[PDB]
Length: 108
Image (tube, rainbow, N blue to C red; front, side, top):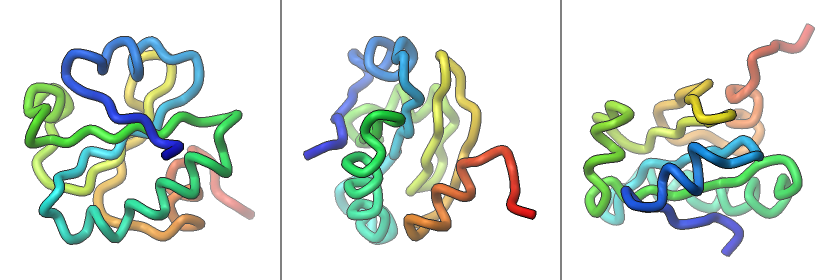
């Protein structure tokens, strides 16, 4: 397991105070599309470990952090950098598609 599990009590230390960018997956155990994205995040967490932390937040056991980032539907992925959210992605995505959508630049 290369992803980290984070909770309402640990979110500030593990995500908001992280040196590395952190990609947070807001998910739930019963959610069909969240399962579609789970193995993709596992791969990214291993492959991109020196550059990026990948964190999982179960919205049902951590409803306050979900409320704090206005998460209404899942999967939602939020990328954090130095304490702020810099990108929000809604919906399941393939690996290549996800990494491209996380960027602020486009290919020419």
